[PDB]
Amino acid sequence: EIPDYLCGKISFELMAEPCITPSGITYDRKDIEEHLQRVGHFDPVTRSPLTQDQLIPNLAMKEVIDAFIQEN
Amino acid sequence: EIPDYLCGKISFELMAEPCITPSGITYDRKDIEEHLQRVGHFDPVTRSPLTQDQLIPNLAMKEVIDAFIQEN
Amino acid sequence: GSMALKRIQKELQDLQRDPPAQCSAGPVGDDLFHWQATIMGPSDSPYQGGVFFLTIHFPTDYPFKPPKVAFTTKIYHPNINSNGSICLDILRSQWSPALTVSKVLLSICSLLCDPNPDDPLVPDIAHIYKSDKEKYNRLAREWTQKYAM
Amino acid sequence: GSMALKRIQKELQDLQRDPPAQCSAGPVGDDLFHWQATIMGPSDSPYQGGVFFLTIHFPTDYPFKPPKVAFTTKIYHPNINSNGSICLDILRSQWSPALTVSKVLLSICSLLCDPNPDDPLVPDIAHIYKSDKEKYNRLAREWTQKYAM
Ligand SMILES: [Cl-]
Ligand SMILES: [Cl-]
Ligand SMILES: [Cl-]
């Protein structure tokens, strides 16, 4: 039983490389980038304009995930 | 004992309004905002340039916290 | 990679543990890329009392491409044509990898309670809808009884 | 505003839980806005076998303003004047609210081990240090014995 907020809004799976967009949404780099490069340059959730360079590595979450991975 | 990644790099207290910087570092809006005003326009940790308008809401983290504020 | 399969398996999990109201869905064979979903005509609509069947085909590069969703049962509706094609922006230009079949399903339902004639697919029905809206329900409930009951 | 006090308290709770190597700190009576700290000679420095006392005064903007830290124990060092004033980056231009007293204490130990003669508070020692290294170690040793032993 994996919480949702630890899964990618695209992959639906746990996040390996979490990173947040300016709209304040976290994706898994590999998936969010596949989207920006094949679908369009917008936030899959807010649809605001978005581009690879605008992705900040959500370090906090990255830890939070490691934590969860320990006890599981 | 609260996990660390769920606390402010400044306040050290649990995070009420977690927002991220382009450095991946997450602070509590209140604290980081005063720092930018009283201390300077740079990331408290990385020290790279930073302005208030660059702070992004770390929503994922906002709910990871609530999630913790659950069992306790 | 075959992330599509992993994504589809997860979606199915969610969809089936909490299915859109009035709806139901599941893979056909062990083909998680070929689903069949069914919808109960909503409770005010002249579609009320009918059972509608649709086919959902997931493209190999899902969820980056939208799913192919079509009505296999006949229906008198302005946004759904004779060969089960549904006109719902979200299934076309407005598709987003973040959306799910469950969401699409919900749209189709609401789209059954509130047709959008300003963006037709079947002009006549769209017209009959705009003007003689009473005649619309007459033929809608008629088709439901003849093709969905 | 009183967040300062809350923060200072966590630091103290933290500090006394896992003291920086060679150091020790604790409140000086009441208001945690005032602390006492002792540092054992850097073993590795000519200050070895010496015990030094410092006073930490937290401003009201803490942690937005660096703590006021000073030696009370006399010490022969180019970066510390006879008033126990310490020329530390991390106490001046390089301060950050992310830094801690603990960190400051390690930084000070580091400084004992390796003085910074180019940014002195005592030109004269800075000189001896850079020119006659030995004379420097001798006096430091002598002063440690006389004032910190
Ligand atoms: Cl994702
Ligand atoms: Cl987020
Ligand atoms: Cl903070």
Image (cartoon, coloured by chain):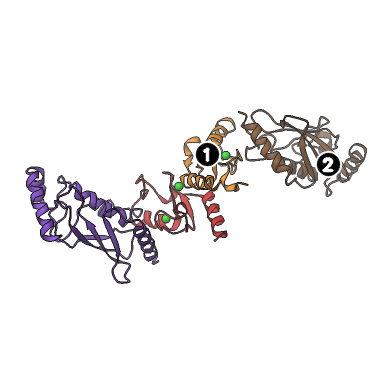
Chain colours: A red, B orange, C purple, D brown
Disc 1 within 8 angstroms of ligand 3 (CB): no
Badges 1 and 2, same chain: no
Q: Name the foreground residue: A25 vs D93.
A: A25
Q: Name the foreground residue: D108 vs D56.
A: D56
Residue, x 37% and y 64% (percent of image)? C9
| Label 2 chain ID | D
Residue that badge 1 annotates: B16
Task: Classify 10 Å Cα crowding around label 2: few (below 14), some (14-19), many (20 and above).
Answer: some
> Which quarter holds ligand 1?
bottom left
Judge from the rendering whether residue C43 lies leftward or rightward of residue D52; answer left or right: left
Q: Name the foreground residue: B47 vs C29.
A: C29
What's the residue type where badge 2 is placed?
Tyr
Q: Position of residue D56 (x, y in %)?
A: 75, 33
Q: Position of residue B54 (x, y in %)?
A: 48, 39
Task: Classify 10 Å Cα crowding around label 1: few (below 14), some (14-19), many (20 and above).
Answer: some
Q: CA distance from mark 1 to mark 2?
A: 50 Å
Residue that badge 2 annotates: D129
| Label 1 chain ID | B
Residue, x 84% and y 34% (percent of image)? D124
- Is residue D134 something one can see in this rendering? yes
Q: Find residue A66 and report its image quarter.
A: bottom right
What's the residue type where badge 1 is placed?
Ala
Look at the picture and state if A25 lies above or below D67.
below
Residue, x 47% and y 41% (percent of image)? B56
Give the number of the mark in front: 1 or 2: 1
Q: Position of residue D29 (x, y in %)?
A: 78, 30
Q: Secondary structure at mark 2?
A: helix
Look at the picture and state if D36 lies above or below C6.
above
